[PDB]
Amino acid sequence: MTRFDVLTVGNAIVDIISRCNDQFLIDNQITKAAMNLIDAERAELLYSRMGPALEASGGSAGNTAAGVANLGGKAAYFGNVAADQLGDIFTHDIRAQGVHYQTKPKGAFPPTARSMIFVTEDGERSMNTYLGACVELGPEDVEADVVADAKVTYFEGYLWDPPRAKEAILDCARIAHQHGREMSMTLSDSFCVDRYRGEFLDLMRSGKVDIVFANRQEALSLYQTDDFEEALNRIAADCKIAAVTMSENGAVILKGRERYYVNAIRIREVVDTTGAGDLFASGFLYGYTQGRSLEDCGKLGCLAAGIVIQQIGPRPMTSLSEAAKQAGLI
Amino acid sequence: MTRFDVLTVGNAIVDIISRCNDQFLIDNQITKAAMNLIDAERAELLYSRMGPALEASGGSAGNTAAGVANLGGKAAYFGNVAADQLGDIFTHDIRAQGVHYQTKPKGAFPPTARSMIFVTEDGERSMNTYLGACVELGPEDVEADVVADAKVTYFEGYLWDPPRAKEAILDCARIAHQHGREMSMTLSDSFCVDRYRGEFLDLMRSGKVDIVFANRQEALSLYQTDDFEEALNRIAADCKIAAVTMSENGAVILKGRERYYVNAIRIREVVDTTGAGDLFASGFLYGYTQGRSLEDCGKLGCLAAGIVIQQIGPRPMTSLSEAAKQAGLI
Ligand SMILES: Nc1ncnc2c1ncn2[C@@H]1O[C@H](CO)[C@@H](O)[C@H]1O
Ligand SMILES: Nc1ncnc2c1ncn2[C@@H]1O[C@H](CO)[C@@H](O)[C@H]1O
Ligand SMILES: O=C(NCO)c1ccccc1
Ligand SMILES: O=C(NCO)c1ccccc1
Ligand SMILES: O=C(NCO)c1ccccc1
Ligand SMILES: O=C(NCO)c1ccccc1
Ligand SMILES: O=C(NCO)c1ccccc1
Ligand SMILES: O=C(NCO)c1ccccc1
Ligand SMILES: O=C(NCO)c1ccccc1
Ligand SMILES: O=C(NCO)c1ccccc1
Ligand SMILES: [K+]
Ligand SMILES: [K+]
């Protein structure tokens, strides 16, 4: 009897969300569908050009932890906010979802991270992230008892951008593995993979990471190829389990030579793709820690992702457990 | 040419929005469908019990001004935030909509007002508002040139709760009337009417207010009757024009002995009624300042209200001008 099914570790971020036209992205040199890092000056500039917005707690791993709790699993989260209103919002939303969260702010500056996310008519999301307080996350923030007591510890590739977060992750990998737990990561973003390609491959090949999440674009970026079949063959050789998502084409779960293909769920409309990969990881990891088959893990991932893309905001506002029951998955 | 069609004046608030069950309201002694004033201690208590939430700029008059701008009218706003992140969000959202907003914060404390709004399955909204920096709004915040150059100055009955806002409003009424403009108010909330019944009647009877907005519950509270026909007859005698909304039953515009009845729009589903009255006022006041008939003003009001109730959050995220064009209201 362990205390947590899934610990996640990521950049703690509040999202600021608006719709825009395609030309807005071009005019402002925003890379479509990507996570674009920005400084404080650029943050104020972009905000001045953004329309009326909505705020919602975000952060890739934060969303994943919230998803696992929503499904009925037991989640914990490490991430660093500031002692400010955005940080209070972030802390409230994750704890109110039933995620064990106790990372203490270090002060009011830098302020809590925020990401201006522009959603185009096709439902694609383009994020512009000022990391703020996330740069302070370090080994001091590792609750060792929580890592030791979690079936899986999952983290963002995005943590390679701030300076010291990787040290916390290496500590987590050591503690998790010494206690017989598993480590998992998401490749996060194809440009993130481009920045840290060798480091990410080393995480997998050295066995610090057991389960890897990627979408098509991230897998292609990892091996610097446009051949998807090649990318799947390569990723399967580099990690114990890979879960690769393909948007409207569903997902494929790889284990050695084993491949499990899962369909995307039928949807009403792609309102906003923000959170899709995060919630895929929620469903997958919930299923995994409940002892379900790899195929069923994929099915739970696709359900949760399919739900989140039909709403504005990155964390489902409806019950995923109720959805899973209805879909005959639980 | 004036500079503004509609100046609005109200409590500058950021909304914190969540769905709840019917029992939540009862367990927490929250008056359903009402605006419930709360202190800082109660705000922290209620927030601790609230689920994960979404934030969106609110304030009844703020919403109204944003609605006028969305329709293509020229709006201005007076309302006081703090120099904090919530205030920054408020300032951004209203200015980004093209509302002329210049009210400077006086410091960081008290913090910017927020309202915890609980939306039940029927789409009714129950608000719990900590006024914060709104208590500092006073005569010093009246931009006399803006009032002088606005065709209509509209304000909330809610302004009677903070201590000095009413003095600002009396100054506005003087300036507006000296420049041949009109004054309008909304009764805001039936308990608000109960607190300030005598004062509201005096505003109307003394001619400080020319156009009054009410819903059924506010009209009934004003005259302390459950006879709606009686309330209509009475309100028509007390103000030059009364616009009275009746939820799904539409609206009626009264001027002397004249009555103009308007149908509600038919709805797919009522998602969240937050902002309905505020956007009815946007549509009405946009029509009024464009020289439209009272019936057409009522039609523009009902269109805007019908749109806002079909989304989460109090300010339409779609184009009201586009909707009005499609409706042949133009
Ligand atoms: N640099 C980043 N690190 C972690 N998460 C991020 C980053 N930028 C944006 N996000 C989050 O990605 C989520 C969608 O996957 C959004 O909720 C947003 O908060
Ligand atoms: N005391 C108040 N004064 C002005 N507006 C309020 C108050 N309480 C809640 N609101 C606003 O009423 C709006 C809905 O009419 C919400 O957007 C909310 O911000
Ligand atoms: O946040 C950044 N780096 C990690 O600390 C950043 C900011 C602006 C531009 C590029 C990277
Ligand atoms: O005002 C807040 N915190 C103290 O500055 C606050 C505001 C909104 C949500 C949570 C906390
Ligand atoms: O190599 C990439 N894609 C596959 O051809 C790549 C490179 C830089 C940024 C994103 C993807
Ligand atoms: O690791 C490779 N690419 C990513 O940098 C690689 C190495 C040898 C052959 C093909 C791909
Ligand atoms: O804010 C209040 N009044 C106006 O300043 C208030 C707060 C809590 C309870 C009652 C009124
Ligand atoms: O960080 C902000 N302001 C300085 O404290 C901020 C955050 C969100 C929206 C606007 C401003
Ligand atoms: O008088 C009221 N309603 C009409 O019967 C009333 C009184 C207090 C609060 C709300 C409505
Ligand atoms: O003004 C009245 N009620 C609200 O206080 C009133 C006065 C006389 C007769 C009926 C209603
Ligand atoms: K979404
Ligand atoms: K609404």
Image: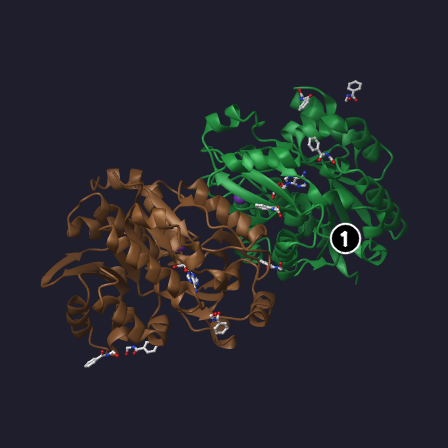
Chain colours: A brown, B green
Q: Amino acid at mark 1?
A: Lys
- Residue B58 vs residue A5, the one in the foreground: A5
Is residue B11 depicted above or below A45 in this figure?
above
Residue placed most toward the observer, B303 or B48: B48
Location of mark 1 (residue): B106
- The image quarter containing residue B129 is top right
Q: Is residue A326 left or right of residue A22?
A: left
Image x and y of residue A247, in percent: 28, 61
Q: How many marks?
A: 1
Q: Is residue A63 left or right of residue B258?
A: left
Give the image location of residue A179, x and y in percent: 25, 50
Direction front: furthest residue: A178
Which corner quadrant of the image does residue B247 belong to?
top right
Is residue B209 among what the camera can see? no
Residue at the image position 79 percent from the left and 42 percent from the top = B165
Question: Dot 1: few (<14), some (14–19), or many (≥20) neighbours within 10 Å?
Answer: some
Residue at 45% x, 65% y: name it.
A127
Q: Relative to B257, is A125 above or below? A: below
| Rendered position, B132 above or below B202 | below
Q: Position of residue B55 (x, y in %)?
A: 54, 48
Residue B40 sits in quarter: top right
Residue A69 image position (x, y, % from top left): 35, 43
